[PDB]
Image (cartoon, rainbow, N blue to C red):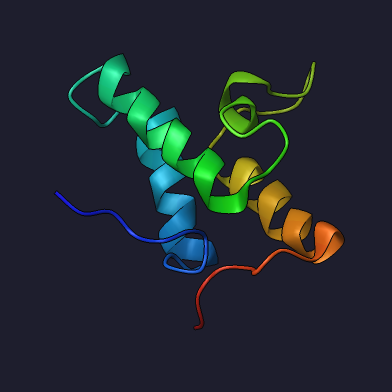
Length: 86
């Protein structure tokens, strides 16, 4: 079909949903849950990329938020393009 460009196409919330549909298992199964995570990778270029979900701190929460909250601060650290505008 046609996705977006990067974290700039999704806001901190719209993007948080993508990670939510991946860590929430609301897709057609784990498979669709991967294309959702890989997209997160090409989005915030983050270091873990698909790890933000497959690499939850040892004792933290893999939830989709703490995952979007960590990235949002990522670009602010690595100076990423950040999400869209809200």
